[PDB]
Image (cartoon, rainbow, N blue to C red):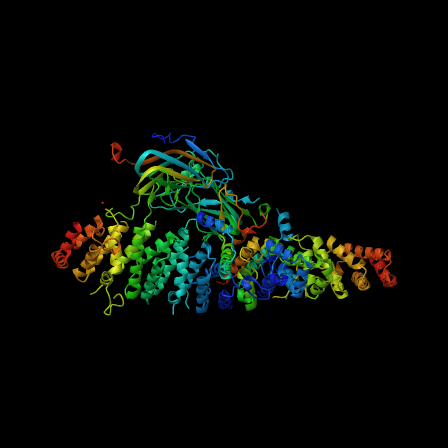
């Protein structure tokens, strides 16, 4: 998760060009990992 | 938990940067990941560490602002509204 | 390390200040503030995490006073938010709210209203919780303003073309308001408001009894007693209003007769009011053998018990007996009697002193001429 | 009013005033007026004549609508499903979620109501109500709370009363919804349901709901309340159960701009001249072009883009750069970060072909720009995302432009633009 | 009009009215042989299918049997197994016109019985 | 509501010549405000019987 969040950090660095599809894949992976680690059950 | 603050701040910037070229479905997961990372750090990330006053104002105006909401039409749809509310609630609950 | 509450307070005060210029939606703002300040089950005793300032509350009340599209969900959010604001540490917030005329305007809007006219148990309970919190927060410091606020609200609702008179608004919530008011202490309440509410309520109930519908249709389940029936729904509301009048006429008056005290009583002022007494007596005269007529009988009995002298009670009765329909005169015009009204007159004439005064005031000649 | 207006200006002034303000006449950077399909249709009818369009232009209408396009595009997020929904689907009309929920009552003595949640309703002539509630003589309301496993976008609530004995149908129904499943909120005042064989409560605005509390009022003429079935219809955020664009998107402004540009050809130029200057207009129009259908078909957006890009050389070069190099906008400023640079579609290929092969003073420069993008791309290959990932379709479009302009006998020196150095660059690229 | 009501479980309404799609009210005028002091009006809806019960009932009374006069605004009757409309003040009536509103959720109005209860001036039926 | 609708239907068949502009403008203003309030203040839920087939107020070109 440290490395995945560093990757997301680097991908979002342009906000602070964005690769939105790559960001989407990374965000979905990070969400799946974090939820494995109730209000969000709708997702 | 400084790198976590960095990534959460950039996620909030991403939320604030979403326009018609961005999509609500991704916004739901961005909000979920923001909330989860904020609540996963040992010293939980507080909303004040993530946003500044203009950024928080824009975030809340996405939920309640009339330039982003038109009554029955809400910014990002009902799911985006619910996800933003849940993310804010989760961050504050982790703080409190 | 730093708390986010100050920042949220700044942002939410800015948002509430944005309501008037229509930059923020009231419903979503209230929902968001309720969600974020409840920390998640709502409870009327919760202190909000996010504290609004006096300007925010004043703007909220102003917007609500003019807000045209206030649906029931909006009203429930409003009531819950007002409750939690009364729980805020700002002068207490409850004092600011009750001292604000916009609060009376807002509650009048709420209570003035294929959907049922009701608001349902949840909205009614939210209104009760808000009023209870106002009462609790003002009890130890200044409950007279809360009681005055309740009486002013009931007066506005009872005045001609008001919610009660026009049969408008949620009946369940109106009845709940009356039930709540009946449990309040009305000491140190100005006599002007007390007399205004008594006058409006007596006029309202007289209109209700005289304007009763020609037909009557109840389901077999329904077994209530009609308003025009003594010694045994809008009837419940009218009966609760009469109960309130009964409570009010018993209030001792202050030395200068301008406020309820805490040996004269509001009953003396009511008896000295010819229009109020005429309305009550004619209303009871339109009744027949607890209902609305029972409420009128109770009010009249209380007035007789609290009258400073038997003459005070006898004068309205003799005035009523000396005129016909709606105070008319004429050779063959005589006042309307009823079994409840006759029973009340007999109770007033139960003592030797009352009978002596009745004789001294021409009562015997009046009744004999009336019989002929 | 438009027909009886003394002059078209009388009708246009209120319309332009409305278009120049936000909600309830508000101002603000991202505030823009509410459009609707009927209102847009009316505006188009008012702008149906050349005189009306001329007045609209003279009164700043074109600039107003273009600025509104850019601003509204900034102020909305696309609710159309994207690759996140595609990924959710890859990971495995409305749908009844009542069967998945658990139904309870606040009255301890109530009969279990799980039978109400069953997807299959009982027989229409079922002589005994599937579920019954006996009212105490002092009870006015009986409550049934259906908790769902997860929050859903609730759209309708169906309650089937016992059809054999309608006297037991609730007299009214108060629906409360809880998004979090804890804090119930009444949707509206109770719905009168006596005399109804079927109770369908449609939410005008779908609400996120993890719990639904139905408070059913005692029947008018019965002490027992009989129900057959309760359905909670709606959608999920994702999955199989997750099944007015002008009102919710910026597309209405683009439809207005297209009408201005195309309705009266003789005015096109003027309109284009009024529309070209506005900042980030081409980026916004390209973003709307590459977005999923939102009330405007691709050909009209392409016509708008081509007519703006062709009204002067500078704008044509900007459009070429937007399509090939950088389509992002040049907290209130437009961003348009959401799309990869240089992505190609039938629309982009057609626009680029028309820009390259349209004969006018700027054509050479446009071709030049195209060729530059080629060489730069090749150069980047020999070692900005639009350069790193040139669309094969866009390269083939440049090739077709060159071929057909050579076969069209253009009025500029096409061969001079195709120098040997570019040819060697392309040869090395292809051999790599 | 029959004095004996049908069986409470009678499966077919004793009388039915089919509403045209544009019809809101169906009227039934009961003329009496002579004027009576009308006190109550009983309407029995088809208990088996209460969806066909009228949504509301407007009662008009004619003492002379020619000029009908509404007693009051229509009484809401949907959800009622029995419709008892009591006149607070008994009215002289030689004709009674019941205007029954189309049911909320049905195109047919089903009734079982109508009773016009009251007294005569004289005779056996003449029983504050 | 029945009597109000009947009144409006009757009024729609009348001739409004030589009517003062003050009253005409007053009625137009009040009616436009009323209808705007009606459309903006629409209920959150919608419950109709199966028999009912009317078109919602916020629906055009039916």
Quarter in which the N terminus of chain D is drawn: bottom right
Q: Position of residue C272 (x, y in %)?
A: 23, 62
Q: How many marks?
A: 0
Q: Position of residue F37 (x, y in %)?
A: 49, 57
Answer yes or no: is residue E5 visible. Answer: yes
Q: Foreground residue, D234 or D315? A: D315
Q: Is residue C6 left or right of residue D13?
A: left
Q: Is residue C232 left or right of residue D97?
A: left
Q: Foreground residue, A22 or C325? A: C325
Q: Position of residue C63 (x, y in %)?
A: 46, 63
Quarter in which the C terminus of chain D is drawn: bottom right
Q: Foreground residue, D420 or D78? A: D78
Q: Position of residue D210 (x, y in %)?
A: 50, 50
* Relative to D8, residue C231 above or below: above
* Relative to C252, residue D199 above or below: above
Answer yes or no: is residue A37 visible. Answer: no
Residue at x 60% of width, y 56% of height: D39
Q: Is residue D187 left or right of residue D396?
A: left
């Amino acid at each position: 998760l440290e490395s995945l969040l560093n990757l997301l950090d680097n991908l979002l660095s342009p906000l602070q060009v964005l690769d939105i599809p790559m960001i989407s894949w990374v965000v979905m992976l990070v969400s799946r990992l974090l939820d494995y680690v109730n209000q969000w059950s709708f997702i | 938990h400084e790198r976590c603050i960095s990534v959460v701040q950039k996620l909030v910037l991403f939320l604030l940067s979403m326009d018609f070229t961005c999509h609500a479905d991704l916004l739901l997961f961005v909000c979920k990941v923001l909330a989860r990372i904020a609540n996963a750090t040992r010293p939980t990330i507080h909303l004040c560490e993530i946003v500044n006053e203009p950024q928080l104002e824009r975030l809340l105006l996405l939920l309640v602002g009339t330039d982003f909401n038109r009554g029955d039409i809400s910014w990002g749809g009902a799911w985006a509204q619910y996800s933003l509310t849940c993310m804010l609630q989760d961050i504050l609950a982790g703080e409190l | 390390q730093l708390s986010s509450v100050p920042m949220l307070n700044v942002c939410f005060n800015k948002l509430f200040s944005m309501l008037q210029v229509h930059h923020v939606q009231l419903e979503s703002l209230l929902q968001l503030w309720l969600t974020l300040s409840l920390n998640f089950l709502y409870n009327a005793n919760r202190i909000p995490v996010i504290s609004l300032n006096q300007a925010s509350i004043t703007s909220f009340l102003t917007v609500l006073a003019w807000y045209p599209n206030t649906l029931l969900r909006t009203w429930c959010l409003v009531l819950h938010s007002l409750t939690l604001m009364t729980n805020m540490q700002l002068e207490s917030t409850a004092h600011l709210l009750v001292s604000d005329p916009n609060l009376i305007h807002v509650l009048v809007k709420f209570l003035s209203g294929q959907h049922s006219p009701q608001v349902g148990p949840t909205a009614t309970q939210a209104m009760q919780e808000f009023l209870t919190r106002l009462q609790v927060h003002l009890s130890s410091t200044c409950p007279q303003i809360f009681s005055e606020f309740l009486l002013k609200l009931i007066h506005i609702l009872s005045t001609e073309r008001g919610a009660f008179q026009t049969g408008q608004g949620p009946l369940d919530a109106q009845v709940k308001l009356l039930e709540f008011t009946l449990e309040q202490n009305f000491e140190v309440v100005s006599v002007s408001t007390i007399s205004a509410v008594i006058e409006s309520v007596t006029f309202l109930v007289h209109h209700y009894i005289t304007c009763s519908d020609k037909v009557m249709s109840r389901s077999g389940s329904d077994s209530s007693v009609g308003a025009r029936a003594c010694f045994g729904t809008r009837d419940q509301l009218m009966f609760d209003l009469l109960k309130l009048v009964n409570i009010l006429v018993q209030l001792p008056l202050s030395g200068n007769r301008e406020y309820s005290a805490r040996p004269a009583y509001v009953a003396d002022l009511v008896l000295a009011n010819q229009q109020i007494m005429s309305q009550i007596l004619s209303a009871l005269g339109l009744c027949n053998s607890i209902s609305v007529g029972d409420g009128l009988f109770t009010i009249l009995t209380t007035l007789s018990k609290k009258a400073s002298t038997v003459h005070m009670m006898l004068q309205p009765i003799l005035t009523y007996m000396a005129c016909g329909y709606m105070g008319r005169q004429g050779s063959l015009a005589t006042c309307q009697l009823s079994e409840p009204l006759l029973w009340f007159i007999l109770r007033v004439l139960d003592t030797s002193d009352a009978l002596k005064a009745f004789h001294d005031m021409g009562g015997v000649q009046l009744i004999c001429n009336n019989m002929v | 009013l438009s027909k009886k207006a003394s002059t078209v200006h009388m009708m246009l002034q209120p319309i332009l005033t409305y278009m120049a303000c936000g909600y309830m006449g508000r101002q603000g950077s991202l505030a823009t007026c509410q459009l609707s399909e009927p209102l847009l249709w009316f505006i188009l009818r008012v702008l149906d004549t050349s005189d009306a369009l001329k007045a609209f232009h003279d009164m700043g209408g074109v600039q107003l609508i273009c600025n509104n396009m850019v601003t509204s595009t900034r102020a909305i997020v696309n609710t159309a499903r994207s690759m996140v929904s595609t990924i959710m689907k890859f990971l495995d009309g409305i749908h009844n979620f009542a069967p998945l929920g658990t139904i309870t009552s606040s009255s301890p003595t109530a009969q279990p109501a799980e039978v109400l949640l069953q997807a299959t309703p009982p027989h229409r002539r079922a002589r005994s109500a599937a579920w019954s509630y006996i009212f105490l003589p002092e009870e006015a309301w009986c409550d049934l709370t259906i908790h769902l496993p997860a929050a859903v976008l609730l759209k309708e609530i169906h309650i089937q009363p016992h059809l054999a004995s309608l006297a037991t149908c609730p007299s009214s129904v108060s629906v409360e919804v809880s998004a979090d499943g804890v804090n119930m909120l009444p949707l509206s005042t109770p719905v009168v349901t006596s005399g109804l064989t079927y109770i369908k409560i449609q939410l005008v605005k779908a609400e996120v709901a993890s719990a639904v509390c139905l408070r059913l009022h005692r029947p008018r003429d019965a002490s027992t309340l009989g129900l057959s079935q309760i359905k909670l219809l709606g959608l999920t955020a994702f999955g199989t159960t997750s099944s007015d664009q002008v009102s919710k998107t910026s597309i209405g402004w683009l439809r207005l701009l297209h009408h201005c540009l195309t309705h009266i050809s003789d005015l096109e130029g003027m309109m284009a001249s009024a529309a070209a200057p506005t900042a980030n207009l081409l980026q916004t129009c390209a973003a709307l072009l590459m977005s999923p259908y939102c009330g405007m078909h691709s050909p009209n957006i392409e016509v708008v883009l081509v007519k703006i890009g062709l009204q002067s050389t500078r704008i044509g070069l900007k459009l070429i750069d937007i399509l090939l190099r950088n389509c992002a906008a040049s907290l209130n400023s437009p961003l348009l970060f959401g799309r990869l640079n240089g992505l190609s579609s039938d629309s982009t290929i057609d626009i680029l072909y028309q820009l390259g092969t349209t004969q006018d003073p700027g054509t050479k420069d446009r071709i030049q720009a195209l060729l530059k993008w080629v060489s730069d791309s090749a150069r980047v290959a020999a070692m900005e995302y639009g350069l790193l990932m040139p669309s094969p379709s866009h390269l083939h479009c440049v090739a077709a432009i060159l071929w057909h302009s050579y076969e069209l006998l253009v009025e500029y020196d096409l061969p001079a633009l195709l120098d040997q150095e570019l040819f060697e660059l392309l040869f090395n690229w292809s051999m790599s």
